[PDB]
């Protein structure tokens, strides 16, 4: 996501684009899986698992 | 009227290096020291720490190195 900033989009625009997807996070204090919205350091996700 | 001796003395030295040879070479060594600093400035021009301390203050050349990218085009 960070490679689109300053090339075809604005920083504030790419952040909104990434936040519409979900990524695996660190497990909580009990060890269960968690999810979080995307960041600029993430990669563009694909349609199939 | 007449001369029967030769008055002389020994000059200060240590090995192959004498005091008279050092005074002859002193002005030239300062130019080499000056020319060595200039060569260092050529090879450290891309170093940002040296840019913010020395090169950015040079008139007509300093402002050239400045980056003016607005924050909205920087990911980091
Ligand atoms: C460096 C070690 C000094 C050796 C030396 O002292 O070498 C002797 C030379 C004198 O050499 P010269 O001028 O007689 O010419 C040599 C023709 N072959 O001293 C100098 O170069 C003075 C500058 C030395 C740097 C201090
Ligand atoms: C020695 C390591 C110091 C690296 C550093 O201190 O800086 C490293 C910076 C980072 O430059 P850069 O990657 O941001 O951009 C530039 C993209 N090419 O390169 C430099 O200065 C170049 C190295 C200058 C020093 C050369 C030898 C001088 C004596």
Image (cartoon, grey):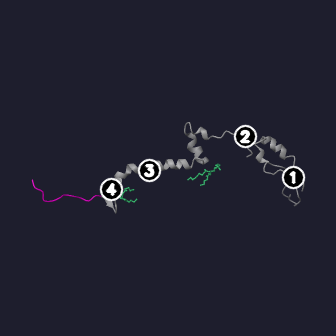
Q: Is residue A30 above or below residue B64?
A: below
Taking B26 as reference, is B13 above or below it?
below
Viewer-side residue, B39 vs B66: B39
Image location of residue B37, percent across then percent down? 49, 49
Do the numbered discs 4 and 2 sit on residues whose CB atoms are within 8 Å?
no
Mark positioned earlier in the residue sequence (4 or 2): 4
Q: Nearer the viewer, mark 1 or mark 3?
A: 1
* Place of residue B56 in the rendered image (x, y in percent of width and height, measured from the top left): 58, 41
Choose top left, top right, bottom left or bottom right for residue B21: bottom left
Label of residue A46 in the image: 1
Residue B8 covered by magenta stretch? yes
Q: CA distance from mark 3 to mark 4?
A: 20 Å
Residue matched to label 3? B32
Chain letter, disc 2 residue: B
- Which residues lie in the magenta part? B1-11
Is label 4 on the same chain as label 2? yes
Compute the Cα span from label 3 to label 2: 44 Å
Badge 4 sits on which subunit?
A: B
Classify residue B32 as left or right of residue A42: left
Query: Residue pushed farthest top?
Result: B60
- Is the stretch drawn in magenta largely helix, strand or loop? loop
């Amino acid at each position: 996501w960070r490679t689109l900033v300053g090339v075809s989009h604005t920083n504030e625009e790419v952040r909104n684009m990434a936040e519409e997807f979900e990524y695996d996070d660190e497990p909580d204090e009990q060890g269960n899986p968690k999810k979080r919205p995307g960041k600029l350091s993430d990669y563009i996700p694909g349609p199939y698992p | 009227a007449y001369t029967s001796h030769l008055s002389s003395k020994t000059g200060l030295h240590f090995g192959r290096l004498s005091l008279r040879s050092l005074t002859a070479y002193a002005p030239n060594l300062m130019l080499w020291g000056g020319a060595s600093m200039l060569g260092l400035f050529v090879f450290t021009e891309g170093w940002p720490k040296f840019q913010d301390t020395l090169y950015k203050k040079i008139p007509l050349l300093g402002p050239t190195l400045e980056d003016h990218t607005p924050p909205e085009d920087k990911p980091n």
